[PDB]
Amino acid sequence: LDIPSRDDDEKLAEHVTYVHMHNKQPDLDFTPVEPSKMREYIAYAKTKRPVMSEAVNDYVVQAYIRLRQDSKREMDSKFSFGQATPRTLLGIIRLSQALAKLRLADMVDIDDVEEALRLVRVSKESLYQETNKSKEDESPTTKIFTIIKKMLQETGKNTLSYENIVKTVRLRGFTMLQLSNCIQEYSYLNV
Amino acid sequence: TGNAILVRKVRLRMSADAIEIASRKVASVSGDARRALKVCKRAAEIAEKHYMAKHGYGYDGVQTVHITHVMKALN
């Protein structure tokens, strides 16, 4: 979907006109390959037949699982690509194998299959917004709170004597004055 | 007979920690005097019936109200 922007119609147009000026789109930093010898190297790569690496499998497998589950909770949702299939997994593997061909190496890299995943996901979310956010950076006391929450998952008590809490805080490195301040705040916050 | 006069001179403590936790819980959702008074009364009478049962005075050393009483009465 071609979002009508401004920097695109600037740069793209400028550079097409620059092609009219200089018939090479390659700018100062570029190594364009003539299609003949390009083809030569490409076929040479095609004559390799690399092998799938044993380590990445799990990761690959896990990727599939992820790419599966979300799909279900995305069936009727916005990005209606429905129920990614085992053929998607196989296509990911094939993409990784071809990238390894580009490496001219017989063992697929974890970076290789990771790049393949990047390709398959960049196909997605390219519809709208194309943005995300981050909130969990600060965490000067909220981190203590989350540690407490894990502890509550363990037992779930709002006790009046904190000895494992202070131990885990000291292990976390956070000081005891900030810890006591936060304890004040949350007791006042009624937890 | 289990009669009380404000034969042993007993004392009673109303542990303010249970009072604290009840106040905290009520102030959380509602913060109502009626609800708090009544839940305090409820835990009180629960402890009362337990103490009565433990000695069987019928109806004709030191006492307290543990946190567990108010825990039950509030839950």
Image (tube, rainbow, N blue to C red):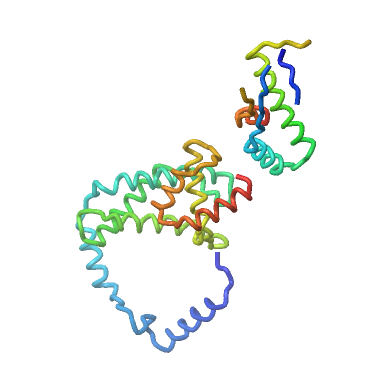
Q: Quadrant of residue A111?
A: bottom left
Q: Residue at x 66, y 27 (%)?
A: B11
Nearer to us in this view, B18 or A133: B18
Q: Quadrant of residue B10?
A: top right
Q: Quadrant of the C terminus of chain A?
A: top right
Q: Quadrant of residue A112?
A: bottom left
Q: Looking at the picture, does residue A70 appear above or below residue A41?
A: above
Q: Looking at the picture, does residue B73 appear above or below residue A87?
A: above
Q: Residue at x 31, y 77 (%)?
A: A32
Residue A43, position as x, y percentages in the image? 23, 63
Residue A167, position as x, y percentages in the image? 41, 47
Q: How many marks?
A: 0
Left or right: A26 in relation to A78: left
Q: Residue at x 57, y 68 (%)?
A: A3
Residue A24, position as x, y percentages in the image? 37, 83
Nearer to us in this view, A20 or B26: B26
Q: Residue at x 33, y 81 (%)?
A: A29
Nearer to us in this view, A8 or B5: B5
Q: Quadrant of the N terminus of chain A?
A: bottom right
